[PDB]
Image (spheres, coloured by chain):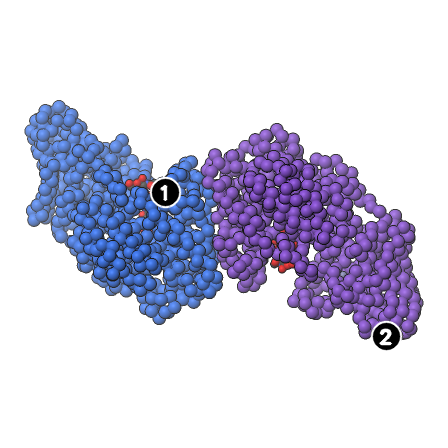
Chain colours: A blue, B purple
Amino acid sequence: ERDMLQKAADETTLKNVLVMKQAWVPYPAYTDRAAWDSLMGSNKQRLIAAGEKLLDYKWQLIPATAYLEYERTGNRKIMEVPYDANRQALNTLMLAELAEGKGRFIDQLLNGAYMSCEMNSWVLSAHLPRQSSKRSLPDFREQIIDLGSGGYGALMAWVHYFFRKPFDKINPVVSLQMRKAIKERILDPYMNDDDMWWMAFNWQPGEIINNWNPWCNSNALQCFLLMENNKDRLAKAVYRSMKSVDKFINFVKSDGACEEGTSAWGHAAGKLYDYLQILSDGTGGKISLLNEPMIRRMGEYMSRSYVGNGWVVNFADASAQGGGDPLLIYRFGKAVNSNEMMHFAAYLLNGRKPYATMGNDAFRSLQSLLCCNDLAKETPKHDMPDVTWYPETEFCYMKNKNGMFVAAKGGFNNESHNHNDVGTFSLYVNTIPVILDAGVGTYTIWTMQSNYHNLPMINGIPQKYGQEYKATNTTCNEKKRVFSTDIAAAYPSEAKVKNWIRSYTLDDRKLTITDSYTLEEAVAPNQVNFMTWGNVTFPSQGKIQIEVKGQKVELDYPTLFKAELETIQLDDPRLSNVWGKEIYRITLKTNEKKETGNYKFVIQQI
Amino acid sequence: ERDMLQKAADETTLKNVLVMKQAWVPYPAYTDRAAWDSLMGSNKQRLIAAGEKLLDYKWQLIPATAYLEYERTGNRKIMEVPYDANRQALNTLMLAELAEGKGRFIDQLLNGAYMSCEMNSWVLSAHLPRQSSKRSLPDFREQIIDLGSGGYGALMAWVHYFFRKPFDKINPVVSLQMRKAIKERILDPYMNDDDMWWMAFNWQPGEIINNWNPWCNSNALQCFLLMENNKDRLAKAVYRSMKSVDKFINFVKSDGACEEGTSAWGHAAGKLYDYLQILSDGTGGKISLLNEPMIRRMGEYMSRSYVGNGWVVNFADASAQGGGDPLLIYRFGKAVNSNEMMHFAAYLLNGRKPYATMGNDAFRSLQSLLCCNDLAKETPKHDMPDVTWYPETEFCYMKNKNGMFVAAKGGFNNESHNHNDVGTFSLYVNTIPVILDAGVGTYTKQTFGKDRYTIWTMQSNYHNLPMINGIPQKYGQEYKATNTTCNEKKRVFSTDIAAAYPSEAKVKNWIRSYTLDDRKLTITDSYTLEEAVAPNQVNFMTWGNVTFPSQGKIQIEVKGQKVELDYPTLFKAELETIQLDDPRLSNVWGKEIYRITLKTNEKKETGNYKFVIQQI
Ligand SMILES: CC(=O)N[C@@H]1[C@@H](O[C@@H]2O[C@H](C(=O)O)[C@@H](O[C@@H]3O[C@H](CO)[C@@H](O)[C@H](O[C@@H]4O[C@H](C(=O)O)[C@@H](O)[C@H](O)[C@H]4O)[C@H]3NC(C)=O)[C@H](O)[C@H]2O)[C@H](O)[C@@H](CO)O[C@H]1O
Ligand SMILES: CC(=O)N[C@@H]1[C@@H](O[C@@H]2O[C@H](C(=O)O)[C@@H](O[C@@H]3O[C@H](CO)[C@@H](O)[C@H](O[C@@H]4O[C@H](C(=O)O)[C@@H](O)[C@H](O)[C@H]4O)[C@H]3NC(C)=O)[C@H](O)[C@H]2O)[C@H](O)[C@@H](CO)O[C@H]1O
Ligand SMILES: [Zn+2]
Ligand SMILES: [Zn+2]
């Protein structure tokens, strides 16, 4: 219950600071060709070309059966593809006309806008079943908001804002309809409906609040800021958005890790940023959380979690490959004043020249034009501390100067997109995974089990799913580079374990993994596993060797263990696109069976 | 002011006799597969096939720019081509699904209906400028009705009627938006707006009432009969529709003749037929002008006017080639009980088996199913009296047993689609034009307003008529025939054409007369002038192979017909070639036609010309 926006002003003080008549708008007027020439630079001629390709684009109809198919077979893309292609084209066209100025894309901008008003809803088939009727087909009677409708409304607003005057010369009915559509599909349902789930009024513990919230709110706000000119009305809506987005802020951890991973980041924390950007712009700076310590942490997670060459720390159900919108990262950085975020984004360009964000998020596409000539001139470096320690989320990254990076976690077995992986670690060498976390396929799914994480099977028994299957006493020593936790309570009763302390210590030349255990009873041998890939050898007892994408390490293990290599064929292409054909589980097993014991494992380059 | 419908019933009568809950509908229940099979005959398999080809039809969106083009450049097709494709597809899919009844086309029918409700309007871009704002782009705030939307409406309503149960199983919001679309776009504008030009409330002398009136009213009425279940509202809507259509019935001439010719007939008299048929069906037989002799004449006009092998009488700005929807001509014929029209329809089939009417007009399409089996059994015959005389319109048709047909007219030079053509004639031999009426051209700017009569097709000079003292007819109401008679038994048309020429003509009397016997047409002129200024000149339009074997003889051989034209030897005969640049004319006539000019030195205040045409 931080309530940081509610604290930063109430409805009344808000009224005094709001900027009316769209004076907040940081882009030029449409008709100011010289000011658009400056901003655009090298973007101009490409955005044009991108418009030229859409001069004969046929705006795609979305038949009823496409929404019907959601109910029938669950197919989403039959509806989403023509929709999204239409959004993209409108956005592209918007960008092209702002580039060229010479009227040439107005006719198509007008068609797109006119078609969009003809549609019954802007809501996706998959999300329409939240309406009263619970149906997949749009009901003219009722509007709700989902991620799509919000983005659509926002782009229709910007196109209204920029193009009303040449639209009104041609025929003033087109802009009139646009204002009716935005009213009836955004502004009105957003004020009159309390119960939309993502608004998070009526939230009680357990229920989810996620990326929907800053995202939809960010778009709602743009609409209201662009389309609503009555001052009492505006203030009422902007405040309602702040009471909603405070509910997201009071649910995410202060340490500022996105616990779903770096793919979710651009639309979770990245949209919280966009909401706070838009709010600041639209109060001339005076309501801004952009200086808050927690927002900068939420931003820097994207840099921290990025190891290199596309390789990201991929806890829970996430991909080992990933990336980011450099142009967003840069803007997010600058705004919160992270030199690390700003240089990181330039590094992420990988020697490319940055061009304007295309896609369908008009805001981001517009904001991408502002940033361009700054980020083009910023210098590429990914420097960061040897340790990052998220104490609440319980994520720990540690590295050394010879290319070893270790991620470690505690947590609990009901994290977002949970994996049963309390205590697990991942080791990268010069960016390349060597002890890996499998990641996301397209708890009887193997990727989900502790069995296929870097963890023991205590008395032979894996981790159970659940809230109360958890780390105790997770600690990090930031100068020593020691992570430690007690994973015992992640295991069910039959594990019969008082303490099992897993610990990770990175020094400049090796990583030392220790387990240290007290059983209530020795029922069956412990088994310890490691995941890897490439060329795994066993050159002598107590020694595993791994050579992969040019890196070479040795894993020393206790000689009481017999190591085997299990091969895992990846049929699932969402795994085989990352790793390839196959990865291995190493299995360390034994006949020994003691009530109290420990193991020590050492990984180093050779 | 006949007011035939208002006389046949007032609102109070109409309510006692209206049929509610669509019990008037004459087609089987969509569910009654055996009844449809029997009705469908061998239509079933060909309709199912038409539907098969549309199972993946992508419904066309109509972009704003398509509507904007009517204002920018006057282009109609950019908008209408996709619209008509959408309708045809929907109408077809309706027929297919009725035929097959297994639910295979329901998804596409559902798509068509839903897509149509998302459209702002069903009005053609060319007609929208009649809306308040006066623009060609739809305005979500306002609906007017035109030929398109009325048509789109009736189709939607029939789709709703047949397919509601299957639609509701899938998702009941579609049929709901269907009921709302029809209501805002048809039922409410029709009820609430007095001032749509085609309704002709507020009609004043010298304003136009035309096919739009019976056409739109017939479609509005369908929507009301299918969609309005409140009897008080329905009766008020139907009575409104009767008041409106009376204005059309009042406007046309009782003698039956459609004076623009047969090319409007289908959607003029044809659509007045549909409207009475619908109204009859609507009132369980009780309100019906189908027994009215005037309606029967209007139907039979199409029969009498159709000479044969594509050729029709073409006074005024009309095409010498014409045709007919046999299935409609049959239904119209049976309902007014005109054997001539029924036999005619069969003749017009040209040996073809009659299959279901496709297109986009749901009413004709469905009605066609009912009439296919009978029309197939009908014997083809194009018989009719030797003489048909339309006395108000001043059209006279005369024919003999050896293959000659003469059309002649008196009239006035301000008829619909007027040609300066008082007194002219057209001669056909075995259905082939021999002395012709050139007909309709591609429109120019000159076509309308002054300069109309600088276009040759429009002048008496290029019709079958004299130039009195070297002067042709003038445009205008007052320039007209006097003493038009027709002796129906002697086959003699006669008329005084003097008053159709201006002052400069200096003409008291000119009697042009036509006599047909069993072999030859005798054209006679007999004139009295005020002052003989210039010599007279007499013209005849023709085509094919024209020769001049001797003085006072002309031979014409065309499409295997051959005649001789005997003319007073006082005249010097020349042949003017008329090359036809205009495709609209060359597609009927070929490369060229000819005007035979007959010039003289003679000059007198009174005199007398005889001409004779017969087969050789
Ligand atoms: C069916 C349902 O209601 N399920 C909810 C579930 O909702 C689903 O969540 C996803 C999410 O990310 O939260 C949504 O996935 C994203 O939807 C976006 C628009 O529909 C789409 O744009 C995202 O894809 C991205 O596109 C960007 C772009 O616009 O260009 C790219 O920059 C980006 O790289 C790309 O990833 C799409 N994300 C994907 C595919 O990863 C989904 O729409 C939504 O239905 C809720 O989140 C959960 C929470 O409890 O409840 C379920 O029941
Ligand atoms: C622009 C305007 O307002 N003009 C009016 C003028 O109206 C015009 O009248 C035409 C007419 O001949 O009556 C109309 O032409 C018809 O329009 C229909 C839709 O475009 C079309 O269906 C007709 O074509 C026929 O369609 C039938 C069918 O499928 O139902 C078939 O049986 C047939 O094969 C097919 O040829 C079409 N008529 C044609 C081609 O002759 C036109 O829409 C309309 O603009 C008024 O008559 C005058 C008089 O006051 O005023 C003008 O300003
Ligand atoms: Zn995992
Ligand atoms: Zn003519």
**Element class at badge 1:** loop
Where in the figure is residue B509, as x and y percent of width and height? Answer: 87, 67
| Residue A127 numbered mark, or none | 1
Where in the figure is residue A48, as x and y percent of width and height? Answer: 40, 62
- Mark 1: C-beta under 8 Å from nearest atom of ligand 1: yes
Q: Name the residue nearer the viewer: A54 or A190.
A: A190
Q: Quadrant of ligand 1?
A: top left
Q: Is residue B150 above or below residue A369?
A: above
3D distance between C-alphas at marks 1 and 2: 88 Å
In the rendered structure, the answer to whether residue A153 lies left or right of residue A606 reads right
Q: Quadrant of residue A391?
A: top left
Evaluate whether residue A541 shows in this view.
Answer: no
In which chain is the residue bearing label 2? B
Q: Give the amino acid type for the residue marked by disc 1 in the picture.
A: His
Q: Residue at x 29, y 39 (%)?
A: A441
Q: Residue at x 70, y 49 (%)?
A: B3
- Residue at numbered disc 2: B534
Q: Give the amino acid type for the residue marked by disc 2 in the picture.
A: Ala
Q: Residue at x 35, y 71 (%)?
A: A34
